[PDB]
Amino acid sequence: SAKETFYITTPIYYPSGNLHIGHAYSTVAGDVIARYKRMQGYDVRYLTGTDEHGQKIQEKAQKAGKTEIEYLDEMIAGIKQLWAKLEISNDDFIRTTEERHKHVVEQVFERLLKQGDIYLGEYEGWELVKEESYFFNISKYTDRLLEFYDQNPDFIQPPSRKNEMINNFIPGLADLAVSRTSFNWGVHVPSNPKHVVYVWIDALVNYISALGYLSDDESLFNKYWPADIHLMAKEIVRFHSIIWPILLMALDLPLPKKVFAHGWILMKDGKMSKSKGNVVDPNILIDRYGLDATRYYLMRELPFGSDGVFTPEAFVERTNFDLANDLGNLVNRTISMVNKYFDGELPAYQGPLHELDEEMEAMALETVKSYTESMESLQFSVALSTVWKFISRTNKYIDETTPWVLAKDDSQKDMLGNVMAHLVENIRYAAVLLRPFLTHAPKEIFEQLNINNPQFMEFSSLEQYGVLNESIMVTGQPKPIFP
Ligand SMILES: Nc1ncnc2c1ncn2[C@@H]1O[C@H](COP(=O)(O)OP(=O)(O)OP(=O)(O)O)[C@@H](O)[C@H]1O
Ligand SMILES: NC1Cc2ccccc2C1
């Protein structure tokens, strides 16, 4: 029967330079939710893309030996290579230079023009800037926007960022300057060609133009709109929670269910900034330490709901202590003992024979429950720390049971077998819960454990502890799961 749809977007990034781990956080965060939602059985569409118009791109191609589009084709090639390297599961990549997007920018602008929502005037702002500009009279939608906030109190996440937008910006909404005559690289206004559509309407409509809105084929739009989550950093929350819902109202379209804004990755001299220069290249981190380590650090160290500071030391600690030592060596210790004592034949689960087992089994279920809650509220660092509490417990379980003492007594084979059974089932739980986060390690762990039944790699298989009630042969050549 038809799966419920879940549409998740990242912001479209500005290719005026190389992307850094700030951009990678948003795209990996989106990828984790997408993979998670697919595992829950949703019909997922995950969109990312590039904002390719503006004076900046013009300058960056002019201050180089190329046309805007040959420059942009180069940068986007590099961005798609990065997402490919990060194993981002985006279902589409929207570019604002492609016809499906530009068509929507022209028609949306002309529609608001014809409705009278956009009118011609002059912008006067701050050096002194003064030029003819089309204005979007958003002020008129103020009352309707506050009613939407009243009916959708969970619209902005986390809730901190909401009361700010309302307290600070909504004073009164001033008419938004939505066009300029001062540059030419962008979508020109059909009814006034010397006008070029500014960032607001151009960038925001990517979420709907990518679903074929106002085209011959609107089937993706009717299927996936409205968006379940727009992801972003805090600096553009007001554009997505004020300008975007008002634009959607003016076009008489359903509004998005949720905007999730995370915090900034900091690097000593403030926010990691493409422009500033204080930049960490995800490619260098993936090349040196591998994909799982780079994905894990991004999602674990930098909590959704606050800012995070990157240090090379903290990266090395997360990689070496959490991944290699805590998880990597739990599996190597377990497989080594199954080989040494049972010659690779893992005895079948029976029940909680040990007195530690009953509450540890209960801990396995309470980990899954705690994980689910954290993931639904987008608390990734808490979801992962909860998983690692369980991994740490599993390591402790080896110490508490002392399997090598049980191996001496020939009458303690039932209990030794039961200890090995609980070790592997604990590892299975951890492997399944990490599938949205780590693309390589879970696969490798199932491989070396010789778990081939694909049902046992899915969330539904965590409902009842002890699914392996058949003898299984684990690898006789265990190797490091990481890097
Ligand atoms: N330091 C950062 N921390 C977290 N997310 C970031 C960071 N920098 C960029 N992002 C992500 O990328 C988006 C910003 O996109 P953009 O292409 O404008 O890059 P930028 O670094 O903000 O640009 P610039 O440095 O020129 O202001 C954010 O909304 C967020 O999704
Ligand atoms: N942020 C940039 C995106 C965009 C699109 C069109 C015109 C200018 C700009 C500025």
Image: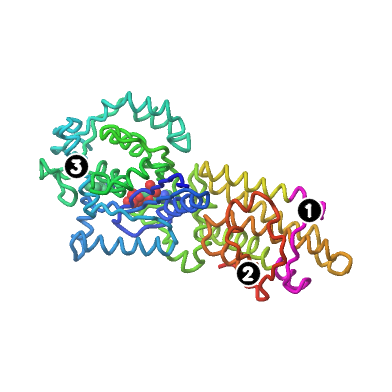
Measured as percent of width and height from the top left, residue 299 is found at 51, 52
**Is residue 137 placed above or below 34 in the rendered structure?**
above
Q: Earlier in the sequence, mark 1 or mark 3?
A: 3
Amino acid carrying label 3: it is: Gln
Residue farthest top in this picture: 143
Q: Name the residue tied to disc 1.
A: 352
Is residue 41 shown left or right of residue 256? Answer: right
Label 1 crowd bin: few (<14), some (14–19), many (20+), radius 10 Å: some
The residue at 29%/47% (across/down) is 206
- Residue 447 x %, y %: 60, 68
How far apart marks 1 and 3 lie (CA) works out to 65 Å
- Image quadrant holding the C terminus, namely bottom right
Query: Residue 310 has which mark?
Result: none
The residue at 35%/55% (across/down) is 92
What residue range appears in magenta? 333-360
Identify the element where label 3 is drawn: helix
Closer to the camera in the image, 94 or 273: 94
The amino acid type of the residue labelled 2 equals: Gln
Task: Give the CA distance from mark 3 to mark 2.
Answer: 56 Å
In space, the residues marked 1 and 2 are separated at their CA atoms by: 24 Å
Which residue is under mark 2? Answer: 448
| Number of the label disc, if any, that sits on residue 107 | 3
Give the quarter of the image for residue 132.
Answer: top left
Q: Is residue 342 magenta?
A: yes
